[PDB]
Length: 128
Length: 55
Length: 47
Image 1 (cartoon, each protein chain N blue to C red):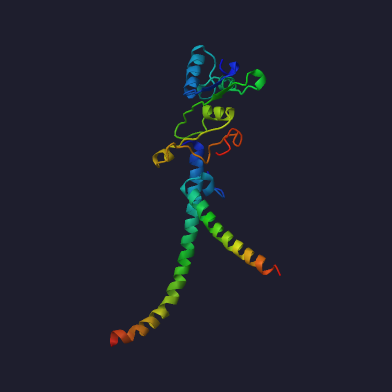
Image 2 (image 1 turned 30 degrees about the horizontal axis):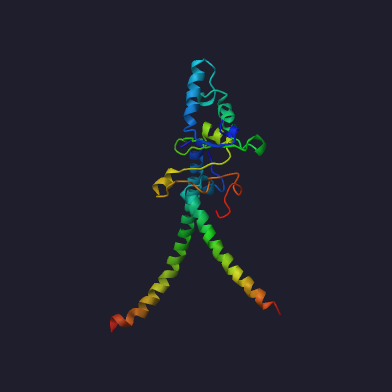
């Protein structure tokens, strides 16, 4: 609504790894056949159709925007898991938080080595 | 960890073990040579110290 | 299960980072030396 009415919005799904679990429970109780790790087949779609709504409308469509900051939770840093990889291949950037950095004193634990942002140059003030 | 983590760690440790075995062999050869060359130098140096402990 | 060349830096454990640093420090030193020599040659070859 906000992005369609020329305003700007920010949405923070927290977590998406629990929406995936709720969807899996629904799908298993409707008797739909399971998939990998018991998640339904349509588990990528579930998220891709959801994170694709965070657009940046041009000035003809109001100019409004909707940023999204999905939050995923990995297991012992296994970024290679199923839902983490799906959402990593869906989103633009990433912000890797690591426990080894959290306890080494670096807080926020952002792992600047791996953290990425496709926009990069653009969307940054000239001084910064 | 997962299977790939364990596989990579196992391969790395195997390489490390190979390298340390090779280095042990090299060090043993160099040690044998060093002992062989140390005997005469042992007598020579002990002689050179002779004076101070005698006077 | 076997082992292959260049596996210590594929795991990326402690030995991988240790080796990467042991390489980078040495080659930074040699690059500094070579750059100094390059500057000296530049100056000595102007004439």
